Image (cartoon, coloured by chain):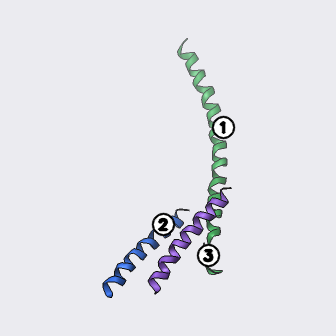
Chain colours: A green, B purple, C blue
Amino acid sequence: NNASGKLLALDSQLTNDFSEKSSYFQSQVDKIRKEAYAGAAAGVVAGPFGLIIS
Amino acid sequence: KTVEVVKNAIETADGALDLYNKYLDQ
Amino acid sequence: KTVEVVKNAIETADGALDLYNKYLDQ
């Protein structure tokens, strides 16, 4: 009877933490895109060549 | 002459990069 | 004359390498 309750207490935590990782994924992909397309905007120290090559 | 202006341009580009990151984080 | 400009070019290349790594990590 103790293990049959520990198993349910593990299953509910699993089904909640999977969704809280699946939201962390979408919150982190946008951070990677922000950092990339924000650091690539510093190619204005050169001409139009240095912008497209960044 | 060339080495001194490249040495100054590297420090100028570093300061410009730091200022751009400081403004963009705000 | 040669030793001084090589000594300046080494420091210029070191600063350029550090600036390139700082920009490439961003």
| Amino acid type, mark 1 | Ser
Give whichever of C3, A30 is nearer the camera.
Answer: C3
Figure quadrant of residue C9: bottom left
Reading the image, the residue beneath label 3 is: A45
Number of residue marks? 3
Q: Is residue B14 left or right of residue A33?
A: left
- Frontmost of labels 3 and 2 is 3
Figure quadrant of residue B20: bottom right
The chain letter for the residue carrying disc 1 is A
Residue that extends furthest to the top in the rendered view of this protein? A1
Q: Is residue A12 above or below residue A3?
A: below
Q: Position of residue A45 (x, y in %)?
A: 61, 75
Q: What crowding class fits label 2: few (fewer than 14 Cα within 10 Å), some (14-19), or many (20 or more)? A: few
| Amino acid type, mark 2 | Asn
| Amino acid type, mark 3 | Val
Q: Is residue A23 left or right of residue C6?
A: right
Q: CA distance from mark 1 to mark 2?
A: 37 Å
Q: Position of residue C16 (x, y in %)?
A: 46, 73
Q: CA distance from mark 1 to mark 3?
A: 43 Å
Reading the image, the residue beneath label 2 is: C21
Helix or strand or loop: what does disc 2 sit on?
helix
Determine whether label 1 and label 2 are within 8 Å by CB: no
Reading the image, the residue beneath label 1 is: A19
Q: Residue shown at 67%/53% (left/top)?
A: A30
Give whichever of A32, A12 is nearer the camera.
Answer: A32
The verdict on a common chain for dots 3 and 2 is: no
